[PDB]
Image (spheres, helix red, strand yellow):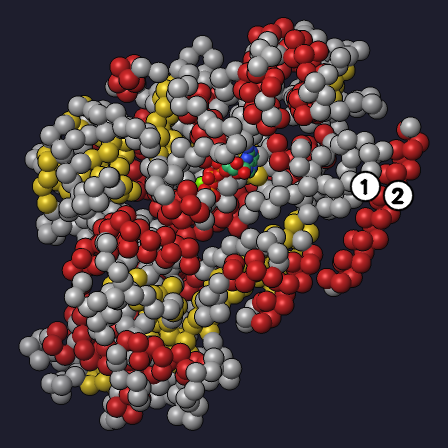
Amino acid sequence: YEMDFLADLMDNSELIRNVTLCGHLHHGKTCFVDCLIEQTHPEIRKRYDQDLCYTDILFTEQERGVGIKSTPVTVVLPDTKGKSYLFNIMDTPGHVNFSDEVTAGLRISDGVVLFIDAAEGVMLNTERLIKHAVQERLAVTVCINKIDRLILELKLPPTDAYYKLRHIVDEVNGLISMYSTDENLILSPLLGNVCFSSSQYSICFTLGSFAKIYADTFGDINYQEFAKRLWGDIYFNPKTRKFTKKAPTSSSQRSFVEFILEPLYKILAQVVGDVDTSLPRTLDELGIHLTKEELKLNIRPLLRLVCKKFFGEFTGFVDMCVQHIPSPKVGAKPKIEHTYTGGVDSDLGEAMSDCDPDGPLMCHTTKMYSTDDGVQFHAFGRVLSGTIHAGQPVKVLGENYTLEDEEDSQICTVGRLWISVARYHIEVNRVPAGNWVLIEGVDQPIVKTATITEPRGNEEAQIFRPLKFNTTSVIKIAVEPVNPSELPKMLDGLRKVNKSYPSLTTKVEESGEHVILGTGELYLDCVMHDLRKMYSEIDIKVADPVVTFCETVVETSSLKCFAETPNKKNKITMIAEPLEKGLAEDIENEVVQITWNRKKLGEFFQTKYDWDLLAARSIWAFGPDATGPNILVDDTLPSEVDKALLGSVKDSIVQGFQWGTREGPLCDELIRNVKFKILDAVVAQEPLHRGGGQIIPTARRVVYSAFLMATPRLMEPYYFVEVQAPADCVSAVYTVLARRRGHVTQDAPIPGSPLYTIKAFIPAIDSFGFETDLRTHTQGQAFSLSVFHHWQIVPGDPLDKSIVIRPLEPQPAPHLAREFMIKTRRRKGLSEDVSISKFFDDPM
Amino acid sequence: PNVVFIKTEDPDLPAFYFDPLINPISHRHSVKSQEPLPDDDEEFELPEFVEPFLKD
Amino acid sequence: EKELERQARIEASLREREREVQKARSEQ
Ligand SMILES: Nc1nc2c(ncn2[C@@H]2O[C@H](COP(=O)(O)OP(=O)(O)OP(=O)(O)O)[C@@H](O)[C@H]2O)c(=O)[nH]1
Ligand SMILES: [Mg+2]
């Protein structure tokens, strides 16, 4: 590959495809791309004993194995027979928190690739990832890595292996059909959306490349006529000399079984066994003529060499990445329709709808990458429209930016451009559209999200929606320095690391604590390592973890919280009650949004929520930030009369509710499952006394009086631990879960290999080392993984001043709720004597 | 990656023997292809003008 | 040799079935 040819192909056409991989716990990714780099960069030779990564440029992934830094790479891959294409592949880690990171980073790719283990098969990360990708409306191209782990490790026959693959594809297609009704992408076992890989042994090909091999050596026309029936349920008929999809003979297997798997196992058994005897007799028939010095290797590298000579240059995956993974000229429409805040009806929408390098520029930086000098970190981003050049200034923008809010803008000169390779970097002077560039000089004004427009002429430009994660981070940790005279360096490192890891979010509570919010234990571990080692060289102290809780109403309020305004001209009354859990999960799952007609919300409430007619028609407002489950309501006999004046002072009431839900009196945390119904609301005709000064805080007082005087109850999170392990480890996992507040959800003998997958919940309070405790007693055979996606109410009722956990015991009583209440109010600095029920009762 | 392996008993069994150890293959019942497939005319027009894969 | 292989397969299948029955009884 010549860099000049790369530049020529860059500003050539939309043939350059954009892809982002997807996998879980080493199921096919960095070894596969190491094979790709060896195919493209021949001088970069892989080792003999140890595996070569080519994706963990940093050190933490090398020392742990679990990748953290998504290292995208772009390669000249002449894998299309008689053609060539450009591929922009975004490598991805596999861990759950890092899976949320990838899901945040999957906005860029027009399509998605999956690497599933041939033996382990489906996992939990994929169970979430399929749903996430279908929610983003991106392409899907399944692939299966670690196939040598099936033929060699298990020593299965062909038919059992093919049935295993059938079951894998059936489960994947069922999950996709449950996610949505994408008939175009669904049902893809043989159309080209199935790649094969043995990354450790470079055994990687597809149906098309297989048919191409046979047509090249001694064969017939291409796979358009042959590969259309190599899939099972159709055997070969040497009598008729064709594939008998009708009733076949007895001693016959599927064309996959006898054309592909037969010689596959043949050469595997000839290279592994009989390496001294059956090597040349089997290799001079179809293989290479490697010298005697080449046969003096161990079994693994020799096998990899033979697999590489067989699949000569891996001309199989470009044949599918161009097939179904669309070009950027095609994917610009839906990607922008889903990402851009406005619709396609905007001038900028139809402008950037095509990948015009000469037009309104709309860049978007997602992942921030550091350099050898920690004081300056670059930024990677997808150029959807326009053409960036060296030294061109751009209007960097923020997530809070808006057409009216011109505060989140800051100009900056693009210093030096690079190309993402993760081992080297190619400097660039001009960048066309559909491009990934390593931006320099823009490191300062960047936030977790980033959007770019032209510094002049790009006016009337909206921004891209803030990305989701599909995994709400619940962990809360404090990080205070060793010596207190090191605050600014620690905070600078904290900000740099925040810009590095988008999943987290800095915070400083009223108690003056330096707080961090992580998704998992290993997430916070890698974060603090990169902090103390890279972004801040100061010795820092660390506390223990704690889960960020929320409040909930156990039942209806007893009395009407009458929070009257201080002007003696506003008497608000809000009675709060809970709602169905599934409806709140759907409101959080973006099922029933707020921007709908009155009839639309009415039908949604009468069908989904099963609410009353006037009840649903009287919808007041939504929850905090229009994303959380906080239902506002306003219905009454005088409410139907004087709703106009109150409607004038309803915006301030909704704002006060949204700001009060952000921090409640229970534990200074969020609130959920609250249906605040406003019954009595005196509204004065004079807006001077009835202004905002007696709108926001009176409403906040009423809301807190209803939430505190209506049988409160906390809500602690529950993870979902899927531990693939044998039966003895199953009993051990039962013991540990019983000893740590567990709840056995599902446990079954997952086929394909002996790994009984134990699916069960763990609370975050008792999740401090679930993986460590499971791997300690199970003798290293129960590598489970957790994901926080289920919040449940603790059984305590922390209102009675009778239970007190004085000593350092772990609150075995059902006063554990009050224990966590006292602990949280002591950690937050607020008044630990939470007795505002009589103070906030507001008697009248 | 829990290293899976099938530790056989003695070297009298075949090489690739399904050890009754793991589970049923799929226990599938939704597949319904008792009747012949539609790719018949082009199938007859789709010969196999090449020697087999590894018959020898 | 073929009959020996079939008998060995039957014996290993019986042994694995007994072991799996014991393991499943313990797990239940
Ligand atoms: N060669 C090979 N190795 C496999 C396979 N399946 C699992 N592995 C193991 O995984 C290693 C390579 O891991 P990758 O597939 O490259 O994983 P990864 O992309 O680093 O994954 P994460 O960092 O966990 O997201 C190999 O050296 C094996 O130890 C397979 O089919 N082939
Ligand atoms: Mg990885």
Q: Nearer the viewer, residue A737 or A12?
A: A737
Q: Is residue A198 above or below residue B3?
A: above
Q: Quadrant of residue A188?
A: top right
Taking the image as drawn, is residue A115 in sight? Answer: no
Q: Identify the mark at residue B9; answer none if there is no mark.
A: 1
Which residue ends up furthest to the right in the rendered image?
Answer: C3
Amino acid type at mark 2:
Glu
Name the chain under label 1.
Answer: B
Q: Is residue A305 above or below residue A622?
A: above
Amino acid type at mark 1:
Glu
Q: In the drawing, does residue A115 fall left or right of residue A218?
A: left
Q: How many marks?
A: 2
Q: In the drawing, does residue A719 fall left or right of residue A416?
A: right
Q: Mark 1 or 2, which is nearer the eye?
A: 1
- The residue that appears at 45% across and 18% down in the rendered structure is A79
Q: Which residue is mark 2?
A: C11
Q: Are marks 1 and 2 in contact (CB under 8 Å)?
A: yes
Q: Nearer the viewer, residue A663 or A563?
A: A663
- The residue that appears at 68% across and 41% down in the rendered structure is B5
In the rendering, at what x and y percent does residue A655 appear?
A: 21, 68
